[PDB]
Image (tube, coloured by chain):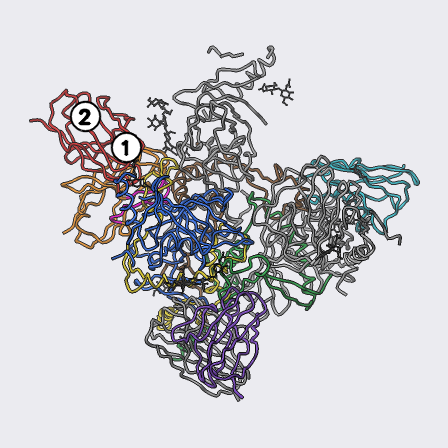
Chain colours: A blue, D red, E purple, F cyan, G orange, J yellow, K brown, L green
Amino acid sequence: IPLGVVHNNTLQVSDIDKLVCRDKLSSTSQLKSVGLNLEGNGVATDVPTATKRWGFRAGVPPKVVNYEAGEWAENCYNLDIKKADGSECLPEAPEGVRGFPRCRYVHKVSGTGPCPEGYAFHKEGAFFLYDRLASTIIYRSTTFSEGVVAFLILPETKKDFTVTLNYVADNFGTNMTNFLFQVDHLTYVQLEPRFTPQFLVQLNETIYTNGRLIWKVNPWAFWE
Amino acid sequence: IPLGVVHNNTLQVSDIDKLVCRDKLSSTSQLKSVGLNLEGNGVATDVPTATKRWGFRAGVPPKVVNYEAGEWAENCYNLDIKKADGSECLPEAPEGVRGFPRCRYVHKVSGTGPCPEGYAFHKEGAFFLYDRLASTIIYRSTTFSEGVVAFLILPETKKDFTVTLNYVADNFGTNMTNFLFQVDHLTYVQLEPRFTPQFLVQLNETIYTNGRLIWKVNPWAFWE
Amino acid sequence: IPLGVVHNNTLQVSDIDKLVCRDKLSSTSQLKSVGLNLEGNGVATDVPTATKRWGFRAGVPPKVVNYEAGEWAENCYNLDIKKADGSECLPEAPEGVRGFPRCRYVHKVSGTGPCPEGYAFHKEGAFFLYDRLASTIIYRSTTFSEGVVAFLILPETKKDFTVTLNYVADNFGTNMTNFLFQVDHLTYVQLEPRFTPQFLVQLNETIYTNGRLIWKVNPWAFWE
Amino acid sequence: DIVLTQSPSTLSASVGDRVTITCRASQSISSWLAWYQQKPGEAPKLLISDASSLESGVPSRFSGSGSGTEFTLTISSLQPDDFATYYCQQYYSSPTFGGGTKVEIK
Amino acid sequence: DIVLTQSPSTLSASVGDRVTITCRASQSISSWLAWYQQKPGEAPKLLISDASSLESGVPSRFSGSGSGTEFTLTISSLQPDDFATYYCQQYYSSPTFGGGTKVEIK
Amino acid sequence: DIVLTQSPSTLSASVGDRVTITCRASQSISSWLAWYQQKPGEAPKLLISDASSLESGVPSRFSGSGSGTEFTLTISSLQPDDFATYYCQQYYSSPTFGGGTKVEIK
Amino acid sequence: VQLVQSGVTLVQPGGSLRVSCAASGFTFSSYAMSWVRQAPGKGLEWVSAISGLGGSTYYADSVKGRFTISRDNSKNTLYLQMNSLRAEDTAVYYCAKDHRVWAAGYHFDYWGQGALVTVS
Amino acid sequence: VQLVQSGVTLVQPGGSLRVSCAASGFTFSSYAMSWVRQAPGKGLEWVSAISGLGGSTYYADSVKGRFTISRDNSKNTLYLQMNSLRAEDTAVYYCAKDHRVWAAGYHFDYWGQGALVTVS
Amino acid sequence: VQLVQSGVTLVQPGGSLRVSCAASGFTFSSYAMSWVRQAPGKGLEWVSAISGLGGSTYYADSVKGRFTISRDNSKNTLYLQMNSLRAEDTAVYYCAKDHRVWAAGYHFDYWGQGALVTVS
Amino acid sequence: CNPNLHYWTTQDEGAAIGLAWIPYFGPAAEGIYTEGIMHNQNGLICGLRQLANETTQALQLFLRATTELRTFSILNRKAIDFLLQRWGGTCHILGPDCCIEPHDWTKNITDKIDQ
Amino acid sequence: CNPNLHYWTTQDEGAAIGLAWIPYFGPAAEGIYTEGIMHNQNGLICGLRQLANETTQALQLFLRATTELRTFSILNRKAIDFLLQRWGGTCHILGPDCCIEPHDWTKNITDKIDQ
Amino acid sequence: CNPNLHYWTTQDEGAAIGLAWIPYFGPAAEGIYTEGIMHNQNGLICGLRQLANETTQALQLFLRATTELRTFSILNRKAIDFLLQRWGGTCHILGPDCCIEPHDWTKNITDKIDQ
Ligand SMILES: *[C@@H]1O[C@H](CO)[C@@H](O[C@@H]2O[C@H](CO)[C@@H](O[C@@H]3O[C@H](CO[C@H]4O[C@H](CO)[C@@H](O)[C@H](O)[C@@H]4O)[C@@H](O)[C@H](O[C@H]4O[C@H](CO)[C@@H](O)[C@H](O)[C@@H]4O)[C@@H]3O)[C@H](O)[C@H]2NC(C)=O)[C@H](O)[C@H]1NC(C)=O
Ligand SMILES: *[C@@H]1O[C@H](CO)[C@@H](O[C@@H]2O[C@H](CO)[C@@H](O[C@@H]3O[C@H](CO[C@H]4O[C@H](CO)[C@@H](O)[C@H](O)[C@@H]4O)[C@@H](O)[C@H](O[C@H]4O[C@H](CO)[C@@H](O)[C@H](O)[C@@H]4O)[C@@H]3O)[C@H](O)[C@H]2NC(C)=O)[C@H](O)[C@H]1NC(C)=O
Ligand SMILES: *[C@@H]1O[C@H](CO)[C@@H](O[C@@H]2O[C@H](CO)[C@@H](O[C@@H]3O[C@H](CO[C@H]4O[C@H](CO)[C@@H](O)[C@H](O)[C@@H]4O)[C@@H](O)[C@H](O[C@H]4O[C@H](CO)[C@@H](O)[C@H](O)[C@@H]4O)[C@@H]3O)[C@H](O)[C@H]2NC(C)=O)[C@H](O)[C@H]1NC(C)=O
Ligand SMILES: *[C@@H]1O[C@H](CO)[C@@H](O[C@@H]2O[C@H](CO)[C@@H](O)[C@H](O)[C@H]2NC(C)=O)[C@H](O)[C@H]1NC(C)=O
Ligand SMILES: *[C@@H]1O[C@H](CO)[C@@H](O[C@@H]2O[C@H](CO)[C@@H](O)[C@H](O)[C@H]2NC(C)=O)[C@H](O)[C@H]1NC(C)=O
Ligand SMILES: *[C@@H]1O[C@H](CO)[C@@H](O[C@@H]2O[C@H](CO)[C@@H](O)[C@H](O)[C@H]2NC(C)=O)[C@H](O)[C@H]1NC(C)=O
Ligand SMILES: *[C@@H]1O[C@H](CO)[C@@H](O)[C@H](O)[C@H]1NC(C)=O
Ligand SMILES: *[C@@H]1O[C@H](CO)[C@@H](O)[C@H](O)[C@H]1NC(C)=O
Ligand SMILES: *[C@@H]1O[C@H](CO)[C@@H](O)[C@H](O)[C@H]1NC(C)=O
Ligand SMILES: *[C@@H]1O[C@H](CO)[C@@H](O)[C@H](O)[C@H]1NC(C)=O
Ligand SMILES: *[C@@H]1O[C@H](CO)[C@@H](O)[C@H](O)[C@H]1NC(C)=O
Ligand SMILES: *[C@@H]1O[C@H](CO)[C@@H](O)[C@H](O)[C@H]1NC(C)=O
């Protein structure tokens, strides 16, 4: 693996075979393992794509890693899924692992589908970030976000360096899914890709004013 | 964490930022992680206080540690507890963990109480010392003692550096507990704080002579 | 533990207290933990001896280790055993652990016996080698081989350094075992020690030609 | 981070009276509060540990109590010497202080 | 280790025709093949990523497809410029090449 | 730590007789005992491994046995050469010795 | 049980100083010590403290890195070297001890005299 | 988006050389680079490549250890020092970039000019 | 299969010495070796031994740290440097080999001659 | 890419605590943490975003060899790799591979020669 | 406090064994152990009793950050911290921070100058 | 004993990969591996066979102390033992225990004395 080092607020990747007497490393406290969000990059972060970013396969052990720090989350994800018969789709979250502690938004989801045997991985090979742990696999009833990892030194300078939704699956993207946000058991919404959390909080509240089964609208990074 | 080092039979704590060229460290065999008893200090070591030294709380992961050496035990403790309904009070001792191997005395106990949800911790934040492992939590049907940990270097000098009782709980110290040692199902004793193991071994044997349900007496470190 | 180092294609064990400025160690990639077969030595490698190489005992934790590389296997072993009552004989293979990936031959076995309580160890204290892990204990329904471990450095030079059978137990070697290879439920063979895998593949195929319950024959390393 | 809240900053009284103080903060504490006193240019003294356990040399006229975030103090009877400055002392996480409290007559 | 297999090594044709190429290898790949072209002494260009996604500047006359081990290419209509050398490019594990393919007339 | 126990320290006999020795220790051993012999100022020899497996050059007149803590030896027939000193040899944990055993006539 | 403030001084800004506080009449190695500020015109705040034997140390945030706690359990003497000075550094600084045993504690027992350290 | 082949040369066997390939008109640090061989009389093969910032590097087996990839994202310039030469080393060597962003990729976009490096 | 005691000597107390025991007629590197004491007037005890190749070594407690086992599998020669001497050190010291293969064993096969090393 | 870095870490610094360390007189759930913010000085954070997307590959491959689930020793191992690069078992103080500063030694040496 | 130190450790020293290491020709339960006793030379053991009661705080806090259950790497990590204090990546043999003894070098240097 | 060494290892070298590292666009089961063969140059492999049969004893005893199941830190620990042998906290560049090559320093020193 590489390694990057802060120095005068400019980063420097230290190629392995290369030698730098100039470096300094006085403690592990200077070292950090940091987990990053895929929200600072401007990717799609909606429930549909979140289905599309993943797949299944078996014959693969589970693989887990630990991180110290990260970045606050705009959005998050959680699942509780079975098959058509009503049989589970996923593994069980072991001990220790916990929901990602920070979530300005939560795209919690339920439903079922075929769920072919395997585990919920990422297309591009990203990670699945939990309370101070990340991995390549989903576990039921748990918060997380998609992300990556960094590895750093810091110098001895003086800097020190909520919401819930609901949905239902529909067959898990077999070229095919209808998504439906839930307000109650007699209310749902045809979900639509380009619509925000905030848009649909407004939607919740305005129908929550207006007496409450399915409806429609009948018709860009957030740091701005 | 600090670190203490033997040198000419006087200890020296090495403050972290401080530098000592004089030091020497030739192996891990010089290093040791030692677990200490709270009996060399003269604290109360009786069954009542052993209840009072603990409490419960949830929302806390379990936390475990490993030690190499320790100190022989005068007293020890073990539990097998449920609730009023007859539902368990504690977690289950996993694999690997085992009773503390040395116990001149064993204050084994049973009974039930409310047992509010959580785990059996220590008031002052001590540890719970098992076979070469310690932690902050109790497990059922297991021997241990309360203690702390040390971390040491040793030099290359040439020095190289039973009993069972029974009891019953009564509601677990809700400002309130009656304690009762057992001789058999038709014999018990109002336990009393200041009375020793040895006193009550004498008591066992003298009633064991005298035909055997509840009785009383009707009326200081051990290294001496 | 010792340590051996390659140098000009001659090995050198580095005694611990001894000092060698000449040594060099630029990475962990130079280090390897290698697991060896007991087939390069010319020992017996037949199913009977494989029973005789082992025993049971309890009061012993399980003990596991990890290795990087090894040597291709001529023969391997797997088990699925219960007691006379039809109760299991062994522990369960946990997660992660897997059959040894390479096996030119597999001496898979079933059956029952007394199976006294304990775990399947090795007489001479060898190991039990699984997918990148070894240990001292057997687990059910898993491939392995008997072996040992090495620990090495390598320099930066430019060198970079199937079959299934079946059997049945008979009481597990209580001075006593009949062994029987299986062709089908109405075919078996009095197994005999000095006969090879290949001999018995020929045997399988020739009877597989000749219409298929028990039969006999009625009458040296492999690198040659 | 955590910030005490003495309440009020000073009192006016007269000897023999019974007097109360309240002290608060931002976050909850498990009865791990302590009290102090000093005078205009004198070194302080301990009064209570845990807001319930008085100390040697302390007159029993005082009475501390509280839990969680809110914490208290009461004096049964006043004295001239007791007209000094008193203080609330967190020692939970950031062993800090707030302003303090004072006594008067007019 | 893995070795592509262009099939065939050259073609003879005539403009406007529709032409196909097949490319194979030893082991399976998950539609992570790419195509290229160059001329006798010219620097190449990208054509397709993943054997299905054409690129900017690419004429739509071309058509790539395939899966696993076998992979393909088709040209709807030919051009003189399209009579150059084309190549199959693994990028799965050992991002290697094989021989290549060529066009002619006679 | 562990300490063998030869029993007795010497014998008196006469040729052709059948003779027995017992050897004990503090803790149990899994038939991992061995025997030796030497003479007054001669280098010893191995006799038995594991207290049951004799060796090449050993006369079959001898007979070792035992288990756990107690261990034994028997000689079918005596010889003049067999009147030498014999020894019990732990090799379990502390590969130690005890006193030894001896032969006589009178 | 007697405590000793030693080195009150007016030192120009950016200066530096080593206070020492001595003690007597108790088991100084078996207790903690600290330094605590009274800025005149206002109240209190905790700065820094020590283990029973010099292993562990603790500082407040405002002066972290500036100051250097120090002790001599052989002399049973406290010390505090201090780096570059500022205005808020103008204040009294006491030496005290905790009520708990073995230096694992807070909620001080007693105080010393205080040294109105100052700048100009 | 313009690429620069610089240093084609005939150098005797066992020689050594540093090629440099420059670039322009894009975010060079935000892309990968590589070196690729055309042996005349036959086809292609991949040699070696780099991360976006010089951390990770990659080589082919045939020349592993011989050659030394190198980059200057300050100049946005590519480099390749090269050790002892042989016959198969007689070939063109291009500099190129990948289609993916942040240098995590393959399946090159464009090419340069190529330098028929040779021996005698 | 022939063994060689070499260096019997009377050396004053506190002295030091290197014994060497040679061998022949077998695969010395493929066996263990040891040193064993006969104190005259009494019986036996095990001192120390070695691996097959000089990696691992073993000592008895009574002389631990004093003595320094040593071997030369090139010469197939055994060695034992020895530090400060005492009275109990007055004894014979043999060189021997184990019955098991690859030096992983005990329960010696044969013996040498013995050297009544002594003090005065 | 975002320049902004509204980030966090864990409250496991040094001097930040009185006695709140006690297990169940402490949160363990949401009050063990630390926050923070920065802004993209010198394109730095987009640089490391690129860096991490480049890291993932070698990460998973370096990972894939073992069978172990919950890795914790990688960071140590990285540090030891650093030192073995720095310290293989032999040093050449002149051979610019060992990274020592002995140059000023000549100061005292010339002070001695002028004795 | 007790001066007396009736203590123990584990039998995992070096040369203490013949072949009893074999797994089930060995106890694994109660006969893998070691005992020992000392007496309070120089107030030493009461000193470390104080030390451990002081340790507990920073121990649990240093612990609390992770999620891992059964910690085993702390002691290594302490050693590496020691060395990084000793060896950050650069040394000043004169600057009394690197802790080398080169002083006697001047012996051979003056032996050469008198050549 | 066998001279022949038809062996294997794991495919966890460095530059061997394009993008096949991706978890489930990769085998994880049988295609993560590496093979190889050698022949007994200098009795070497029979030598290490002897070595391993000798290793087993001290291995299991060094193991037996802990309670931990799946050991992974032994190899590190061996390396740190090596360095502590090399580097205990103090060095004697002359005392042939620290293993530095300063001898050529005298070259520049005599270059200075001839100034
Ligand atoms: C490291 O050293 C520290 C001290 O330096 C030890 O910790 C303290 O030790 C003292 C004495 O051992 C403890 O004092 C006892 O505390 C009990 C707890 O009371 C709690 O509950 C009541 C009621 O809710 C509250 O009012 C109170 O504030 C507490 O929250 C008291 O009840 C005890 O009082 C009884 O016993 C004493 C002793 O005989 C009698 O004199 C009293 O009259 C009364 O009958 C007692 O005062 C103190 O609680 C400990 N606290 C802490 C935080 O450590 C550690 O034990 C030591 N380390 C280890 C590992 O042991
Ligand atoms: C590190 O950086 C890399 C790139 O450097 C990122 O990875 C690539 O990112 C791009 C863009 O983010 C991805 O492009 C998208 O790929 C989708 C996957 O399609 C697959 O399935 C189809 C059908 O089977 C195949 O034909 C195809 O070849 C793939 O196998 C496409 O479907 C997307 O197309 C749609 O979206 C785009 C974007 O708006 C539209 O313009 C299109 O018209 C279309 O609607 C899209 O092209 C690419 O797949 C990523 N691949 C890889 C391997 O990385 C990483 O994301 C980044 N790291 C992390 C952790 O994120
Ligand atoms: C490392 O190297 C060591 C030796 O240096 C190997 O270990 C020894 O290897 C030898 C030969 O391989 C083994 O010898 C065999 O032991 C069997 C075990 O018998 C036990 O049970 C009987 C009955 O209770 C007892 O009497 C006996 O003392 C034992 O307790 C014997 O039964 C064998 O005898 C049979 O086979 C031989 C071989 O052909 C025949 O000649 C005999 O006549 C008889 O039929 C045999 O002698 C020895 O047991 C091993 N012991 C130990 C402790 O190692 C290791 O194998 C090697 N390391 C590894 C990992 O393999
Ligand atoms: C949609 O919005 C409504 C409020 O606008 C949510 O309902 C309230 O949620 C708050 C959250 O603290 C509760 O205190 C209230 O009790 C809720 N209202 C009622 C009537 O109970 C609702 O949870 C949101 N989400 C949906 C409907 O899915
Ligand atoms: C109380 O003491 C008696 C003996 O005085 C204990 O009973 C005996 O315990 C020994 C322990 O080895 C056994 O061998 C005996 O068999 C026991 N006696 C009988 C009659 O069985 C008794 O266990 C002690 N504890 C109690 C009664 O709780
Ligand atoms: C014995 O040998 C026979 C073949 O000679 C085995 O049976 C065949 O095994 C192959 C393995 O790929 C299968 O494809 C065939 O279908 C099998 N034959 C039939 C009729 O199904 C057999 O498995 C071997 N082992 C035994 C009989 O135990
Ligand atoms: C989805 O469509 C593609 C072609 O566009 C097809 O290959 C694939 O099989 C389809 N999925 C399913 C589940 O049929
Ligand atoms: C125990 O008594 C205290 C007051 O002395 C009280 O606050 C507490 O609630 C009581 N415990 C219970 C369980 O009621
Ligand atoms: C096997 O035979 C031996 C004697 O040869 C005997 O000691 C042992 O008890 C026998 N095994 C059983 C299970 O009886
Ligand atoms: C040794 O001397 C040469 C010139 O003679 C100089 O360039 C070199 O830097 C010196 N060595 C060191 C380590 O400075
Ligand atoms: C260098 O010389 C000064 C005096 O000139 C001396 O005090 C110092 O100790 C010397 N350096 C070392 C490392 O001894
Ligand atoms: C120092 O000088 C002596 C002779 O005076 C020489 O033998 C020795 O090797 C020198 N030191 C070093 C480290 O070479």
Chain name for mark 2 = D
Closest to the observer, J80 or D85? J80
Q: Which chain carries label 1?
A: D
The N terminus of chain D - image quarter: top left
Residue A30 can be seen in this image: yes
Label 2 crowd (10 A; few <14 / some 14-19 / many >=20): some
Q: Residue at x 20, y 31 (%)?
A: D37
Q: Is mark 1 on a helix, strand or loop?
A: strand
Please report whichever mark, 1 or 2, sits nearer to the chain's N-terminal start: 2
Give me the C-alpha separation between circle 1 and circle 2. Answer: 16 Å
The picture quadrant where one finds residue D94 is top left
Give the image location of residue A161, x and y in percent. 32, 54
Question: Which residue shows up at 57% across the image and 78% down it?
Answer: E8
Q: Looking at the image, which is closer to me, A73 or L67?
A: A73
> Are the residues under badges 1 and 2 in a single subunit?
yes
Answer above or below: position of E1 versus A194. Answer: below
Q: Name the residue under label 1.
A: D33
Percent coordinates x, y for residue K48 in the rendering? 43, 39
The residue that disc 2 covers is D20
Tell me where residue K11 appears, x and y as whole percent: 59, 42
Q: Position of residue E73 (x, y in %)?
A: 50, 73
Image: magenta residue range: G48-63
Q: Which amino acid does label 2 sit on?
A: Thr
